[PDB]
Amino acid sequence: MHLMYTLGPDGKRIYTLKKVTESGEITKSAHPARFSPDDKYSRQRVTLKKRFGLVPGQ
């Protein structure tokens, strides 16, 4: 039962994951406070289906 959907900032199904390879720096898609992390807005089907591009790096 992997892959999660969020309806917070908008309300749809923010695609993401929790498994080991769950998004990048960010906790997973969605917004952390300001347009930063992928948010699941990194066009799915790209890369390798892992994470959504990440952003809140360090």
Image (cartoon, helix red, strand yellow):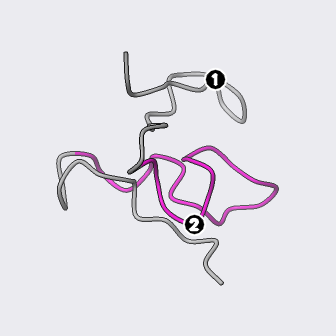
- Mark 1 lies on a secondary structure that is loop
Which quarter of the rendering shows the N terminus? top left
Evaluate if marks 2 and 1 touch, with contact meaning CB atoms under 8 Å apart: no
Please tell me whether residue 40 is drawn above or below residue 14 in the rendered image.
below
The percent coordinates of residue 47 (x first, y second) are: 19, 61
Q: Which residue lies at the image location 82% right of the left edge and 55% below the top edge?
A: 33
| Nearer to us in this view, 27 or 44 | 27
Q: Amino acid at mark 1?
A: Leu
Q: Which residues are magenta?
A: 22-44
Residue 49 appears at what percent x and percent y? 23, 48
* 11 relative to 43, above or below: above
Q: Nearer the viewer, residue 20 or 53?
A: 20
Specify whether residue 52 is painted magenta: no
Residue type at mark 2 is Glu
Question: Would you place residue 19 above or below residue 22 in this image?
Answer: above
Q: How many marks?
A: 2
Q: Residue at x 17, y 55 (%)?
A: 48
Spatial CA span between label 2 and label 1: 21 Å
Quadrant of the image occupied by residue 58? bottom right
